[PDB]
């Protein structure tokens, strides 16, 4: 016990501060203030925060599935996602949330609105809407369900032998969802892997994903004052010869930098894009009360060659800033007929199309690296 | 293309981060035509594939 | 007892954080973390900083900084100082100082980064509402001095213009002698635009010239003792003189105490735009053998029982900045142009300056209305 | 003169209601903004009302 220096301060504050506050409020401010002051990433997860961490790392969410966008400072829905109970109901793009269970909106931020709207999946809820043509509200009574958000998806590229794989965050679904996504396309000759903007997630999915492609050696190593640990490939990897080009960006951080760093140090892929965020540590999450937890930075991590990235990111092999591709000055005179025949349905989101490759020069650059690798394999098989 | 978004957040900007532990082709020439940049980016891919196979 | 949660949290932090830290570090972080979650204005002083503060009795940019909607913002730069010349403005948000990010720092941290020895350079990055990008300013620190107050006569009128740029010492004598040197005058324009604050005893020292009786302002916390109340004394020389006061979003604190006291006693007309509400006062307290805390202790209350936090003062007549309108219809017809009409039987404020801001014009037009109501009633 | 802190041209504050009407019986704030001489005539009545209320003794 040496808490006297602190106990004097809480004693002086409750006596001389402007307003009335309790020891329960002062101790809560001191706990959330201490963890926020150890390093950039330690934190206190009270009961309103801890439920979000569980939801995001499971991939399961309870609510409406309507994308609210704060247009003009008001609760306009940009898009319902397909197959959610609210998409089965009559709400559409451009609908505005006026009231929740007949309680009024007031240009407030989305945070407490979704805190009210995320009732448990067993219970129906009422929402009041304004649709832009109407002088009167629309009222929806919606029976609920759990909804699933996929963190990873895979597409063919329409003209060529190559796949596009997007991983948007790390969670328990990722390793299984990539493995089945390659098994469904046995004709494929290479992967573009898109980690742009991915903030990280569970550490066992960074080791899991990178072990789909590397056969032998260390993947990552940890150090800290207490016993420290090392991860090695299990020897059982599929896909050990397939070409990979990986895209990284200034928003890529933490677990995203573990897999991009492991592939770079083992010469297993080409790294393309811009310099990353530079987060070099691992954090452990501990329950401390019945519905409250703490997150505390517990180790630093090292890439297979013994280097580390704390406060300086991964540097690409090929550097390229964002923009649209250059154009031919002839362009068929911009013929409005488009070579369309006009002689007279498809799920075309099955494939990536040339129009939306021309809109992203970083994606074009990743495909042109795969086309170079395919030539060197056809040379070297002699 | 060029780096317009110069101001953006990094680990080195945060409050309590853990600490660290004439006769040649110039970069100014390579920025003026994207065709010459694309040739060098293809050679950088080839050098990595050789280093893998060795 | 009450330390159950805290002692559990401290035990994990000592056990399994990345680096070796002692209880002396953990208690110090818990103190600074508590005050930073209590209010925007508080601070902790260790055994070096607390004596260093007592030892110091100068140099800087002359920016005044204030917390609004969770961001550091400029209140107003003073007219003489390097930041005013450099093009810093009210309502600018401060993004970086010498490449340190402002994302998680107090008003007291930012002031201690800015203050320093004269001729030392500094760099600041700012966000401004109309701009496509952040603006970078490079400025050299100094110890400039200029008078806060001046009095100028308005050309072709009975009226005086009085400027008060900040409530530093001697403002009462500087204003009073300017009036005593102009005994023929018939009204004041008092310009408090862009005035960021100053000394309370000088602010009530100004309004005691113009109000004879009653409460000027009052200071309150949760305790009954130390609930100070400030009242006028009967020596006020100028009880009948007309006044118009100018205020805008760069005016705060001591400049709002003057405007709110004159408005509640009906002694003046308040003109311009809503002020920046800054109604709180803070005190410094020793807490350990050789350490201190700064914390907010009381709020200010106007004669009507309204408080300045965070509403400020609203003017009686609202008008935004701009130039006056002008006469195009110059060729129009008059009696003097008809055939066979019956016949007839520079140390001063110039018109060219008054035409360049309509806020100053509107203050003079109010003094003209007041002068007519006096002449009617006499 | 007009405030630089624009409302981004929002339609009547999202044309608010919460559940002809002889509007031309009254002068609106929109039709005062179109005539600076009419605004100036009202500001004189505001000044006179303060000075006359100070003299309630």
Image (cartoon, coloured by chain):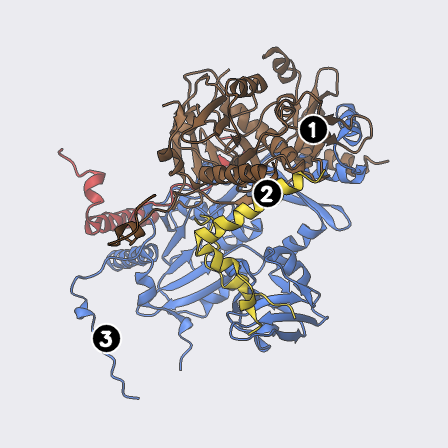
Chain colours: A blue, B red, C brown, D yellow
> Can you name the residue that lies furthest to the right here?
C1
Asked if labels 1 and 3 touch by Cβ distance under 8 angstroms, the answer is: no
What chain does mark 2 sit on?
C
C185 versus A310 height, above or below: above
Q: Relative to C294, does residue A242 appear above or below in the rendering?
A: below
Residue C127 screen position, x and y as percent? 44, 40
Mark 3 crowdedness (10 Å alpha carbons): few <14, some 14-19, many ≥20: few
Q: Residue A220 carries which label?
A: none
Give coordinates of residue D13: x percent, y percent. 54, 61
Whether residue A268 sits left or right of residue D41 in the image: it is: left
Q: How far apart are marks 1 and 2 (CA)?
A: 28 Å
- Judge depth for marks 1 and 2 and give the one in front: 2
Image-based side of A204 in relation to C357, left or right: right
For mark 1, name the chain: C
Q: Mark 1 points at which residue?
A: C295
Label 2 sits on a secondary structure element that is loop
Q: Are marks 1 and 2 on the same chain?
A: yes
In the drawing, what numbered circle is on residue A336? 3
x 42%, y 69%: residue: A185
Task: For marks 3 and 1, give the one nearer the viewer.
Answer: 1
The residue pinned by badge 2 equals C314
Quadrant where the N terminus of chain C lies?
A: top right
C-alpha separation, residue under disc 2 versus residue under disc 3: 60 Å
**Chain ID of residue with mark 3:** A
- Evaluate whether residue C342 shows in this view: yes
Discs 2 and 3 lie in a common subunit: no
């Amino acid at each position: 016990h040496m808490f006297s220096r602190f106990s004097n301060v809480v004693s002086e504050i409750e006596k001389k501060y402007v307003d009335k506050i309790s020891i329960s409020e002062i101790m809560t401010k001191a706990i959330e203030g201490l963890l926020s002051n150890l390093d950039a990433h330690s934190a206190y997860l009270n009961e309103k925060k801890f439920k979000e961490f569980q939801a995001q790392t499971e991939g399961e969410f309870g609510g409406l599935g309507i994308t609210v966008g704060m247009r003009d400072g008001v609760l306009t829905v940009i898009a319902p996602l397909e197959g959610t109970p609210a998409y089965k109901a009559g709400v559409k793009s451009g609908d505005n949330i006026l009231k929740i269970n007949n309680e009024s909106t007031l240009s407030m931020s989305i945070d407490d609105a979704i805190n009210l709207m995320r009732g448990k999946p067993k219970t129906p809820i009422q929402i009041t809407i304004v649709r832009k043509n109407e002088p009167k509200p629309l009222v929806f009574n919606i029976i609920r369900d759990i909804i699933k958000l996929p963190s990873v998806y895979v597409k063919k590229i329409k003209e060529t032998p190559y796949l596009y794989v997007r991983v948007s965050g790390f969670d328990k679904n990722v390793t299984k969802s990539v493995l089945e996504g390659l098994k469904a396309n046995p004709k494929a000759k290479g992967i573009v892997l898109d980690l742009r903007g991915n903030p990280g997630g569970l550490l066992n999915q960074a080791v899991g994903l990178s072990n789909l492609f590397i056969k032998e050696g260390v993947l990552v190593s940890q150090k800290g004052k207490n016993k420290s640990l090392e991860y090695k490939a299990n020897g059982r990897a599929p896909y050990t010869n397939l070409p990979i080009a990986v895209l990284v960006n200034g928003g890529s951080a933490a677990a995203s930098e573990i897999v991009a760093g492991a592939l770079q140090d083992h010469k297993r892929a080409v790294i393309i894009g811009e310099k990353t965020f530079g987060a070099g540590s691992v954090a452990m999450l501990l329950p401390v009360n019945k519905d409250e937890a703490i997150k505390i930075t517990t180790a630093r991590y090292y890439l297979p060659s013994g280097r580390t990235i704390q406060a300086k990111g991964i540097t690409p092999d090929i550097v390229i800033y964002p923009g649209k591709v250059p154009e031919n000055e002839n362009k068929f005179s911009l013929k409005e007929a488009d070579l369309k025949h006009h002689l007279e349905k498809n799920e075309e989101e099955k494939e990536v199309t040339p129009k939306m490759i021309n809109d992203d020069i970083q994606l074009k650059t990743a495909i042109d690296s795969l086309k170079t690798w395919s030539i060197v394999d056809e040379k070297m098989d002699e | 293309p060029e780096n317009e978004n110069k101001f953006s957040l990094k680990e080195a900007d945060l409050k309590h981060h853990l600490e660290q532990e004439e006769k040649e082709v110039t970069p100014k020439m390579i920025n003026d035509d994207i065709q010459l940049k694309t040739a060098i980016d293809s050679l950088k891919t080839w050098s990595i594939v050789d280093e893998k196979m060795d």
